[PDB]
Image 1 (tube, protein in one colour):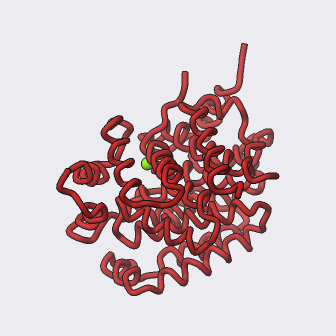
Image 2 (tube, rainbow, N blue to C red):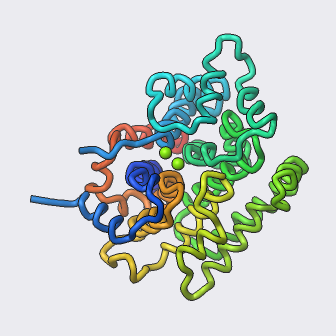
Image 3 (cartoon, rainbow, N blue to C red):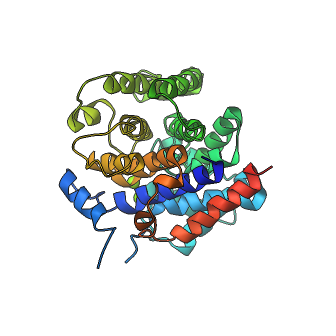
Length: 339
Ligand SMILES: [Mg+2]
Ligand SMILES: [Mg+2]
């Protein structure tokens, strides 16, 4: 499979995760049968599903990378802010809105200061850095640039290492996804090596200990994925208890990744006519909690790995702006991949 296909699959899967997972975000628990009914209603026979903050930001991040042919924090920050100002009602978290509103100040002149000031200088560790980061791994091909620019992109709104390290991790998973066919063993191992190295930094260790998490929390969770995957049958309750399904990056980014890995194999609960990308998005949503973001992150990874061949037209064409999202992928491929 060729890499425009992976680029297109990445962004479309992210878009599907948002658009479809967003239906379940206010739900207590999620009924699997209801998710199955809903995705089946996308097919037939004989109204778009709206995207939210997660795709709005992912797009504005891509657009910045395209306009500058590189990461440029002043441009990206301004695009984030203007996209909010244009369409403020996409469903942004309250915390991120305070940052945008500071960014829209004429007297703001350090774009990283607003984010840094949040939670009394601790910064946010929510998943909003990670929800939008996929573009970084489509623009930057070296693992080093991916880490660097995923951190700085996240830092525009999420100044906590617990936040930006999750963005890094999600950027690395999509990066490794772009290399295609792997064992889940090999895939996790590579992710672990990177996060064990990142979480040894003194800032990451202070931030974890201050939160009272004792440290290397992304590394700890990547090891738990390891044991979940090698357990015969693991229930949703057990996944959510070990990994999380919440808004914090550490409760969502690893979960998105177990969903990707687990769903590489069939599941008798999910009709066997659904392909692996499909299964991933269904399974991701069925865990509840922060369904729009977990599924958009899991869709990003799945899409990069499986490509547009597993993105059905009926699903894709149900989503608001699926046409702009294909253009975004084609432009990124041309601007960054073709050379
Ligand atoms: Mg959302
Ligand atoms: Mg969300």
